[PDB]
Amino acid sequence: AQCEATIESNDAMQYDLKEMVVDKSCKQFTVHLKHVGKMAKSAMGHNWVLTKEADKEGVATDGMNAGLAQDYVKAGDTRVIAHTKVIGGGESDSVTFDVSKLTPGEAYAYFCSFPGHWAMHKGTLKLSN
Amino acid sequence: AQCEATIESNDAMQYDLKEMVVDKSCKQFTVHLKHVGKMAKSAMGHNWVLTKEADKEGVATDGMNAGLAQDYVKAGDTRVIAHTKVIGGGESDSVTFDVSKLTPGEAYAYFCSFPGHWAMHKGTLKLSN
Ligand SMILES: [Cu+2]
Ligand SMILES: [Cu+2]
Image 1 (cartoon, rainbow over the protein chains, first blue to last red):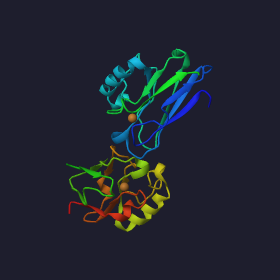
Image 2 (tube, each protein chain N blue to C red):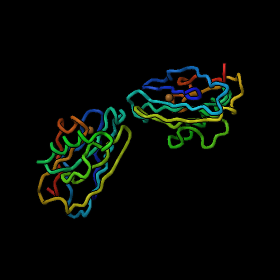
Image 3 (cartoon, each protein chain N blue to C red):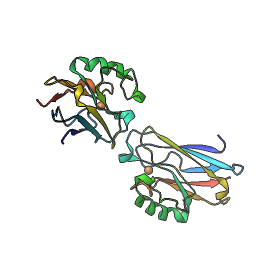
């Protein structure tokens, strides 16, 4: 694991982890998102999107505008550090990102941009400590 | 319409159609299954299978033993005239078949072979009635 983490979503609007740490010696980090509840993505789909705190709302706004075929992230958004696909019950998806995109010590927002989800389904990630 | 019919399955094991009539001016017929329920396929997957009424249980049984990955139909089962894949909530799938495989006035059985679902409903398909 070390430069890898699994976070879970279910049929409610919270990840099991509300905080995450990337170890400073990680060159890359992989997040595995598992949807462990039984609802289909048309009813309760979820993703994991990482941005700087200040970019969360713009990414969530343009995100819900992007539609499910874009996994509710605006195509090629420069403000998205990393994002998974939208998954439904029984599915999972991973994303590996460049740890040099993270300023050490800065708190970063990770949230779900699925319709209705962005303000509830969220947490914070930081590079080591 | 024409030589196509759409049938919907929800999160109770039933179709909105109990009798499907293929018309004799059709060379091919296309069924569009829509799973209008909201649960994921691991929880409430549905499909549509067409066999002769004498073969409904044998195909269903071997199908149950074929597993979700094999769309609950045994691969290359000579008794299956047509089948879709097992789909989840919010999904759709279609199968087109050649009407020369059907005999005048003979009643055929359509069913979902997802374990149990076949035994709690009955649906018939005939050529022009
Ligand atoms: Cu969500
Ligand atoms: Cu079914």
